[PDB]
Amino acid sequence: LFNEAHSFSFRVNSLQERVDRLSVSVTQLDPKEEELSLQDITMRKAFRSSTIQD
Amino acid sequence: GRFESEDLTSIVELDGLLEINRMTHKLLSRYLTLDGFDAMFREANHNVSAPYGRITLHVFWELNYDFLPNYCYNGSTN
């Protein structure tokens, strides 16, 4: 149990760092910097969620 | 994809099917944990990382090609 829970502690700590970075990044967005691409552009890499089945 | 393979009149079918999917997600979320239906819909519509999704692109494509040059209006019935 201790070994397993220690792994979760590492995962939680890593997530905490990511959230702190995102919060700093999201509180800096400038609305004037937003730009939109052409209507006929589909070259953007479609986002795919993780699908790992044990 | 099914909507993308038919004319603009399939919008009602897409909305009905989407409502069914949303309700199924709500039923499954009672006992399981799942991502929000909005996030999954955006993921399937390629809208999370892009300003415009697939549905709007198809609507524009249909308007330019089929709807505009193959439909006659009637103001009496709108």
Image: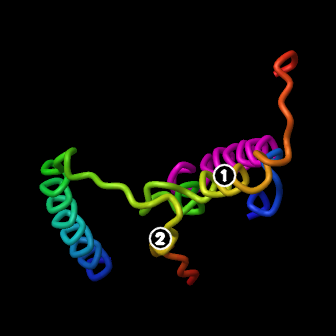
Residue type highlighted by circle 2:
Phe
Residue at horizontal 44%, vertical 55%?
B51
Q: Chain of mark 1?
A: B
Q: Is residue A19 visible?
A: yes
- Region of the chain picked out in magenta, as a range: B11-39
Residue at horizontal 55%, vertical 77%?
A51
Q: Report the Cα–Cα distance between label 1 and label 2.
A: 24 Å
Element type where label 2 sits in the image:
loop
Element type where label 1 sits in the image:
helix
Q: Is residue A49 visible?
A: no
Please tell me how crowded label 1 is: few (under 14), some (14-19), or many (20+) other residues with Cα within 10 Å: few
Quadrant location, the C terminus of chain B? top right
Q: Which mark is drawn over residue B28?
A: 1
Residue type highlighted by circle 1:
Leu
Depth order, front residue of A20/A53: A20
Residue at horizontal 71%, vertical 47%?
B18
Q: Where residue A5 appears, x then y in whole percent?
A: 29, 74
Quick check: do tags 1 and 2 share a chain? no
Q: Is residue B30 magenta?
A: yes
Which residue matches tag 2?
A47
Depth order, front residue of A5/A53: A53
**Helix, strand or loop: magenta stretch:** helix
Q: Where residue B7 appears, x then y in whole percent?
A: 82, 53
Q: Where residue A49 appears, x then y in whole percent?
A: 50, 71
Q: Is residue A10 above or below residue B54?
A: below
Quadrant location, the N terminus of chain B? bottom right
Q: Is residue B31 left or right of residue A9?
A: right
Residue at horizontal 21%, vertical 44%?
A31
Tell which residue pokes out farthest to the top in this image: B76
Q: Is residue B37 magenta?
A: yes
